Length: 55
Length: 175
Image 1 (cartoon, each protein chain N blue to C red):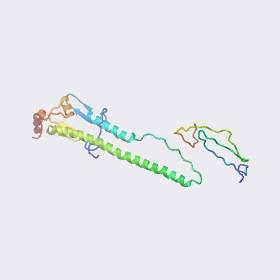
Image 2 (image 1 turned 30 degrees about the horizontal axis):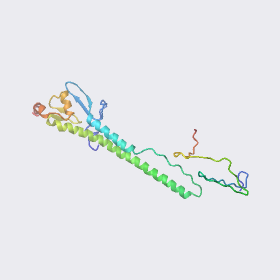
Image 3 (image 1 turned 90 degrees about the vertical axis):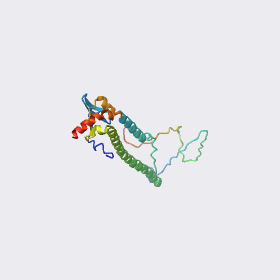
Image 4 (image 1 turned 120 degrees about the horizontal axis):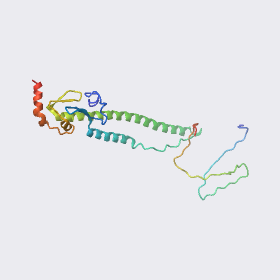
């Protein structure tokens, strides 16, 4: 069904890469390759808040 | 209340007594005035601080868990999460309200007991040498100077020392 002027669909995926691990890509079509990835470290005491309150 | 002294046989408080929770008011030839009883007030302050500590010290602040998000095919675990959140909230809300109510009743009774115990200590000492005139007040059958007054507020009052005096005045109105 046409959503936002588009009869097609795109599904977005994600994963995590361990240190010293290789990730491989292989396709003959229909691949939207990553360009900008992210390196991160977990804090502990953080979360997500849904609000309209000003900052 | 539970011990009959506060709002009981001692009808009201002393606004003019600002330096303590319990104590005495005296009146003799030297002078008058309110004076706090250190021992009862000091112990009671320790007890209430212990009581408040025993409630709040173990209520350490904690890190609240992340508010979970679920999709349309996760209603069962969404409801389970809602059941968990609601279950804990009801218990803490009900217990905290009920605990404070029960604790507050004991706090007032504790103050009532300390007044009654303080009154009994004085009554146990004076015996026939003074007349119980109600409202927690004693009228002496003998002259009690400032030095004599502190002996009553100490547990030292010498009944035989004023007995011969107080006996004569007692039987004088008794006859």
